[PDB]
Image (tube, rainbow over all chains, first blue to last red; front, top):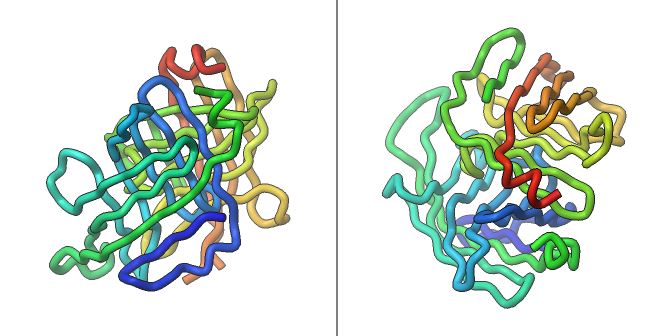
Length: 118
Length: 111
């Protein structure tokens, strides 16, 4: 089942992983759209991280977008099993200050539905 | 793409990426960092499974089907989806929303 760690703290994930694809992209959603936890990878092998969202972490929405230069991310793939690690970043909207940076790890195994869609 | 919440357009500027598997379509706006996404079935009309709207005036807003909280419906015309409903959040906030997006031919190929 899905594992999400933020700043060295296991998140208590009660939900499910949903994996979808189309040419170029593998979307991994953990907990449904309302959480905002998701990662987007290329459909290549080796994979590349396009973006990560960690949702609202203590009032700040943290994420990674490839090509902005802010935060960082790395992925590994073993079939349907993906691991993404890095540093996510964000700014407090209510009280914008310096960017917040937090380490993360996401590990999931997609279902056979993702194999079929590829 | 257009995202409206409580009658206010959010000025989303990012890309729309529509992906599928097993009868579900995920629409993501601005990549994962935004938290803006919707999950629909591949039916006529599509049924809304979930919507995330991100952080909006301090609260994460969204919708999950089957809980009895909020509401959402959708229509599909070609590659274009319109999703409207009521989203909710807590630190209870209820806000109307509308998402309008056109997916690329990459979704039609995957379906």
